[PDB]
Amino acid sequence: DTCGGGYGVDQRRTNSPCQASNGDRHFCGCDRTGIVECKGGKWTEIQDCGGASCRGVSQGGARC
Image (cartoon, rainbow, N blue to C red; front, side, top):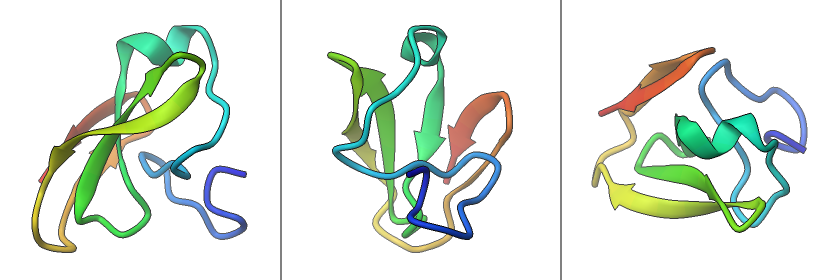
């Protein structure tokens, strides 16, 4: 459910369940327009990149 299919390395699906360790990592939405973090056990937007150019790594560190 990282992206309903074709998810990236640092891309996650919003309103989706995340891991416990994910709570200490950042991921850029599949739209690459916003950044979401693992909160309350679910991926929630914490930052807005504005443009679809946000890219991160498999280890997190999501950046615009």
